[PDB]
Each structure stands twice: as structure tokens, then as C-alpha cells.
Length: 505
Ligand SMILES: Cn1cc(Cl)c2cccc(NS(=O)(=O)N3Cc4ccc(CN)cc4C3)c21
Image 1 (cartoon, rainbow, N blue to C red):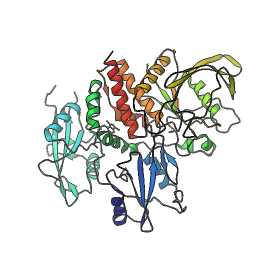
Image 2: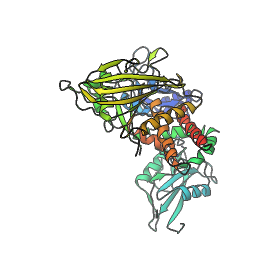
Image 3: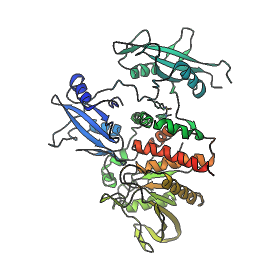
Image 4: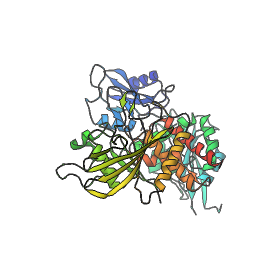
């Protein structure tokens, strides 16, 4: 993901494209003052165009283009579909040649600030064979150091060790005292990852996994939120975003012509390997097996389905899915309407009423209002088959703000606690459905929080959580799960709040 430049101003971006790019060169960058605002800067005709990309929490919105689940998916889409991006005039803007960043600050293995003993101590306590990091040399400013652990993963017996390797910076290029000079640390690290260094006496300094500092015991969260609150949240979030290059899995079924009008947004699509497949379709319907939805399985375990708000033409498919998967609990993440725009289409009957949605039949038995949500008790059955009836409990969250995130996580936490006890009380209930909007932002945020508090509920303080690792695992099952830095911070705040209420228990 070299085309993303975290610490660049607009005028710096222009100068890079004009002096080191050509027509078709391009890069993306953030605004520093306005989080969630991004810019795509592109060269055309020896001049530079800047195109804004907005994320309020639900998707990336490219002005003059489409909506996307990640910046990597945006770039992949426009590098394979020419003529497709246009300016105000309507003229064509081509993304041909990514302009690569050399700044290493968003790489998992970069820990600029560490000293040698502090790096030895981290690798000693937290690392295993092949754990590595790169830090700035203290004794030679501008130079860097590579620290690596190697040995037997079975007390302090002498079967393992840390080694250090010095990295010179000479005329803006990096080397290990011999061989090739590299244009950046990334290229040097990538090269020795594939072709590790060997000491004369045989030891192979294998670079297998970056040092892990985000795995922590649950009673540490309080002091870690404090550290991260003093732009650390930004750094850690952006480090996670630079891993999304690894999650470009295929979405071919969602691109079929037969399926185009089943998607809220044409390029926000379900991965093929985790999509929910519908069986028992009307035999006439050429393609009856598609819904924009994915199974989320955390890696007596709870699983989820993350999905979009219905289209008026996908309401029947939504009920086919709930029935087939045996789901007994639904969470809605938005109002029907926000800012005068449809965010989650009504797909249930009015209170006390009964409606048929194709082959499925739903009764709305009772609504109950709470402060932050409405609960609707629904009864779902197949038409013509009496005792297929099951209760489905629909939890509609109603107080999420239109932009950003709640200022207090208590409401969300009290909501998931109730949703969790309902699910546990029903024997053999299927996955919990979580949906509305495009089903990636709020939906990802609710699911991740739920996974993390589950661990803490079953274990207690004596449990390791790892927030960015957990999100990466859920982003491998649906595109773009958790959209913003505000949502990312919200998840840490929710975990902190949950711990501090049980620590009063
Ligand atoms: C463990 N894990 C797995 C995935 Cl995928 C992932 C993505 C991002 C972050 C971490 N955690 S980490 O311990 O590797 N990590 C914290 C952090 C914070 C700042 C920097 C400076 N760029 C570097 C690092 C390294 C991840």
C-alpha cells in the first residue's frame, strides 16, 4: 500500500507528482485537522488534480465517483476500469502509476523510539523465534537498527537470543554494510524477509513476525488508553489500515449482472469465501442464491451475520436467510431515516399485524420501547407449514448520532449485554444478524465490541485481548469492517468502560 502518504501536505503532494511522477501518477493522503477526510491527488496534462474522499462512518465517498469499503478496494477498482473516474467537467482522470511513499512510520515492524535494552526486553518478554523490529540508532542519528529474536520456543535456558543489525543511511539509501543499497526501509525489510541474513557460523536471522505490543491482559487496558490518548490512537489505527492491502479477496458472485440490483452500492460486495448462500430458491429464478451478507466466525462460540439494510427487492431474501440460518436475534444499527435519507428500509409488519414476504410469514407480536432502542417480538414461519414458527427478537438501536460515534459507550454496552443474554437463553439459536446502511461501519463496530467483551465476560481480567489483530481477522471475512478512527477509539473506550463496571461488581 505504498501509494498512501500519511504525513504529506497538499503542496508537498503536488511537488512529488510534478517532479517524480508523470501523467497518470497518483497518491492518496489524509487531512490532519479533519479526520475522516482524505484526498486522491492525480497528475493529468502536466497539472495536478485533487479529489476529496469523505468517510462519516459508513463508507468512503469519492466525489465524482462511487462508494467503497476501503481505499485499497477503491484504487484496485479504478486501476482496472478506465474512463470511469471524472472531474466536474466530466473529463477522464486515469490512475495509472502509483507514487510510492518511503516514510516507514505506519509499518507494523517500525518502532522508531526504542533503545537497545528496551528492544531486547520487549523481544525477550513478548517475542518468539523470528520476531523482529526496526528502531532508530541513538548513537548515529539518521541510521537505524534491526533487532531480531531467534531460538527454541520451548525458562531462560540459553536456547534463544536477540541479535542487532546496523542500518546505515547514505545519500537517502539504506544498507547493512554490503550488497544492495535500497530506496527505503520497507524495500530493505521486504528483501531480507524473502532472503534472510546468515551469520558465518550458520544462524539464520529469519524475519517471521513483527514484535507484538497490542496483545495485553485486560486489566492493562486502563493505562494503555491513557498512553494512546496523549495521537497514539491515530498511529495505531493507521498501522492497521496499511494492512488492508492483504485483504483483497474475490467478490465475483456479487459482480454478476443477475445480482447487480441486490446491492446497496455496486462496489461494496461480499467476499465469495464467506458469503451466505441461499438454497431452496424458486426454480424459475436464474440466480436465487445471492444476498449481500457474510458469516463472521471469531478466530460454545457465538457467530454473526454482517449485512446491509434491505432494498425493497431484497426483503424476501433477507427473511429466507433468517429462516435458513436459524437466527433468533437481529440488531439494527441505524434509524429507518437519518438526514432525510433512507438508511434501513422497513421489512417487518406494524405492531399486532401479520404479513407475507414471499414464502415466509411474519407476525409483529409486541414492541417495547427502551431509552436507546426498541425491541420487537416477531414470529417467523414458512407459509403452509404451521410448526416451523420461531420467535425472532429484533433489537433496533435508535440513538447513534448521525455523524461520528456516541460520546458515552454505556448505552451500547447495556444494549449488547441484553442482546447477549437473549441469545444465550435460546437453545441452538443460529448466528446473530447485525445490519443496516452498507453493513460495514456501525455493524463492524458493534460486532468487534461484542467479540471482545465476550472474552472478558467468560474469563475476567486474566485474559489477553488484541484489538487491531481482532479487527484484521473480521476484515478478512467482510470488506472494511470498522471504517473510522473514531470507531476504533470507541471500541477501546467501550472495553475500558465494561472492565471498570465489572471492577465495581
Ligand atoms: C498484532 N497486529 C496484527 C495486525 Cl494485522 C495488526 C495491525 C496493526 C497493529 C497491530 N499490532 S502490533 O503490535 O503489530 N503493532 C502496534 C503498533 C503501533 C504503532 C506502530 C508504528 N507504526 C507499530 C505497531 C505494531 C497488529
